[PDB]
Image (cartoon, rainbow over all chains, first blue to last red; front, top):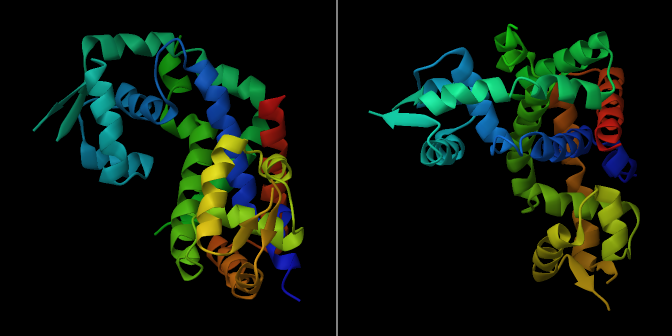
Length: 136
Length: 137
């Protein structure tokens, strides 16, 4: 009997997949004013904390390979938010200015999660533990 | 204020979720190669292996996916001869039903790779379920 092992409700992957999509849906609404997609927003988070990073450094930080990150950088550059120069990525004046408009986003996500601070930190910790166990 | 601390990558629950999901996805690209399926196509098979002969709507509300997202997947499953379409209503084929036996190795390896205890895995799954619900409400 192998069926119970494959029931949808018993898959850790599906819970992760569906919660991540729900998070994306929430962000599409939260990032509307700053015209960013979630992954693009992640790149900006990296730059707003540490500017002038190489593509390799950003990819290592976000756990993204070149093929997935490059399109994000291209879109950010075309929007005038970052520069790409031989590759090193840096914020433009408007890209740096965008940070002030994203200040309320984290709090909005915290509220929507319905988690207490400890529940959020505990969940985040377990997810990071899982990420480390799954990845090389 | 120190809006910089609120915006740090390492302080985002969403990133921990996004990156753990990505790691799980990468693992699955390797695991599913033996079944020659993509993750979403696999999810559809999971639904059918538990409850066969389902409508596109039923499969959708089970996976929290809309018809527009499911349509391409079902056509690929059909082309692979794992599923048939009866006009709406998706049913497993002999081949699709047989694929279940070898699919068991997927959850098996995921558990091993997760380096979690049974209790830890189900507890994390429960919290993620709670979050999905909360985010949508």
